[PDB]
Each structure stands twice: as C-alpha cells, then as structure tokens.
Image (cartoon, rainbow, N blue to C red):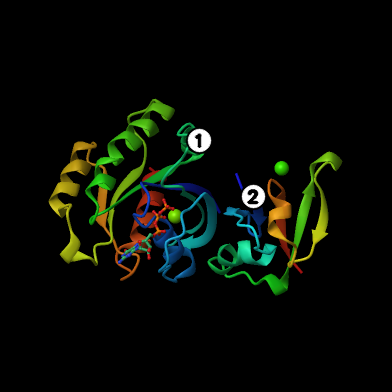
C-alpha cells in the first residue's frame, strides 16, 4: 500500500493533537500538554483502498521557525487548524500557508482548512462563512469545521487530504 | 533543553519534556498511552552513537533527568 505523509499545522491550543489522537486512537485528550514533536501511523481504508498514513503532529509554538521548513518539504498534505474560539489562531494561518508555498514554490499544494472546537458554539469568535471565505480566497482550498470532542468531521480531515494527494 | 527523543514501534516517534524527579516511565506514559502501547510489554533502549547505533537496554524506572539529550528506542518484548 502507498504511504501518505500528512502534517497537522496551526497555533497553540487549537486541538491539533486532540484531532490527531481522536483519529488514530479514538480517545479524547482533555488535558493540554504542549507538543514538541509527535508522529503517528494508522492503516486506513480510503475509497475502498488500503492506505498507510503517517501523521506529523507539530508544536503550535516553535522557538526556531526554520524547523517548520523541514517537515513541510517532506509533507504531502497539510491540515491548517485554527480554533473557532480564538481569533488570533485564525489570523496566524496566513503566514503558515505562505511558508508552505515558499518551501515548495508551487502555488498548488494539497491542504485543508480546519475550524476546530465547533462544539463550543457559545464561545465562537470566528464565523463559519468567515472561514469558508478564507478557503475560497486560498484557491478554493477544502474547508470544514470539526470537533475532536464531539467527534465531528475528524476522519474527514484526513480522508480528504488523501483524496487530494492521489490527484 | 530538557528533552529526550524516543523512537516507537510502527515507525512512530515522540519528543518528551523531562522534569527533575520523573522516572523514564513517567516521561513516556502519555506518549505510550495515546498510541495504545503498554510499557510492561515493551523494552526501552538507549542508542549508542559512539558504537554505530548499538542499543543498550534500560530499566523503565531509570531517572529521566540522567537521560536528557539521549535518543531512545522502545521495542515490544
Ligand atoms: N471543547 C473542545 N476542546 C478541544 C477540542 N480540541 C481540543 N480541545 C481542547 O483544547 C486543548 C488543547 O488541545 P491540544 O489538542 O493539546 O491542542 P494543540 O493544538 O495540539 O496545542 P500545541 O501542541 O501546544 O500546539 C485541550 O485542553 C483539549 O482537550 C475540541 O474539539 N473541543
Ligand atoms: Ca544525543
Ligand atoms: Mg499538540
């Protein structure tokens, strides 16, 4: 089976780890323990095909930003995650996407914009349309709101990246 | 930087923070749990770079602070 190198990116506290662990282990991480570097692997059936996924879960805050260049080069697909309850995390994604494009030099890179923590509707400070508009602005980049807690659109983030990869 | 990089089964890896007082089992508990791995069913080794990747087995109760900067590997028994 073909292997897919997926990278989960985004600012601190958005739920990159919670989403990843929910997808791989099917459990919800309630505590917030900042990631330094973590990789997971999961055998998954996408479109009736066996796929081996290698997911790189990244640190929301890197002392040396240049470290990101290293995993973006190897990464095939990228998930840009922000929290709908934190505006700054949504605004931080612009620089991240430009860094991804700067590393590959190609304006075409399979990715998905993810507005996480959608179960916290009362604390929403980033609109759904607002996120959909950013995605549209990013050359019709895929978009979805998810919840690592309520298990909403968790699998979809990764399944979609695989679809984009096999072009 | 008080960290340790650890290579895990199924070609996975994790870098964990080490706080004085923690044993090896303590620093790796969460990383193993979220991957469905159990320490009692695994052996942990210290990679010996001065001897071309040779592995040296460690006790799970080893003082973690003494391993800062070391690269470890966890294999199943
Ligand atoms: N309610 C809710 N909480 C979530 C969700 N996803 C994550 N969290 C919580 O948000 C907090 C931080 O989660 P992490 O998954 O550690 O986020 P992170 O992006 O990996 O942060 P860093 O590794 O430091 O960059 C934790 O306390 C989680 O339990 C979600 O969908 N809903
Ligand atoms: Ca070393
Ligand atoms: Mg994390």
Query: Residue beneath label 2, please?
Result: B5
Check the residue under mark 2 and report the chain it is in.
Answer: B
Helix, strand or loop at label 2? It is strand
Camera-nearest residue between A127 and B10: A127
Q: Quadrant of residue A145?
A: bottom left
Q: Pick whichever, B63 or A124, lies toward us.
A: B63
CB under 8 Å between discs 1 and 2: no
Left or right: where does residue A86 sit relative to residue A35?
left
Residue at horizontal 47 percent and vertical 41 percent from the top: A75
Q: Quadrant of residue B43?
A: bottom right
Q: Identify the residue at the far right of this view.
A: B51
Q: Residues within 10 Å of mark 2 (few under 14, many from 20)?
A: some
Quadrant of the image containing the C terminus of chain A: top left
**Residue pointed to by mark 1:** A67
Disc 2 CB within 8 Å of nearest ligand 2 atom: yes
Q: Does residue A47 show up?
A: no
Question: Where residue A148 sits in the image (x, y, percent)?
Answer: 35, 65
Left or right of residue B74, residue A144 in this image: left
Check disc 1 and report its element: helix, strand or loop: helix
Residue shown at 46% from the left, 47% from the top: A59
């Amino acid at each position: 089976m073909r292997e897919y190198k997926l990278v989960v990116l985004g600012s601190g506290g958005v739920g990159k780890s919670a989403l990843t662990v929910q997808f791989v282990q099917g459990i919800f991480v309630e505590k917030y323990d900042p990631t330094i570097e973590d990789s997971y692997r999961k055998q998954v059936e996408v479109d009736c095909q066996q796929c081996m996924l290698e997911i790189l879960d990244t640190a929301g805050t890197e002392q040396f930003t240049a470290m990101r260049d290293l995993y973006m080069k190897n990464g095939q697909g990228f998930a840009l995650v922000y929290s709908i309850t934190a505006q700054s995390t949504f605004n931080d994604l612009q620089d991240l996407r430009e860094q991804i494009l700067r590393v590959k030099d190609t304006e075409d890179v399979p990715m998905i914009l993810v507005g996480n923590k959608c179960d916290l509707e009362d604390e929403r400070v980033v609109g759904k349309e607002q996120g959909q508009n950013l995605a549209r602005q990013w050359c019709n980049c895929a978009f979805l709101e998810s919840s690592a807690k309520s298990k909403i659109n968790v699998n979809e983030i990764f399944y979609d990246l695989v679809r984009q990869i096999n072009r | 930087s008080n960290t340790i990089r650890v290579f895990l089964p199924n070609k996975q890896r994790t870098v964990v923070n080490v706080r004085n007082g923690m044993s090896l089992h303590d620093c790796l508990m969460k990383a193993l749990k979220v991957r469905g791995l159990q320490p009692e069913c695994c052996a942990v080794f210290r990679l010996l770079h001065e001897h071309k990747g040779k592995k040296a087995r460690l006790d799970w109760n080893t003082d973690a602070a003494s391993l800062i900067g070391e690269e470890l590997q966890v294999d199943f028994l």
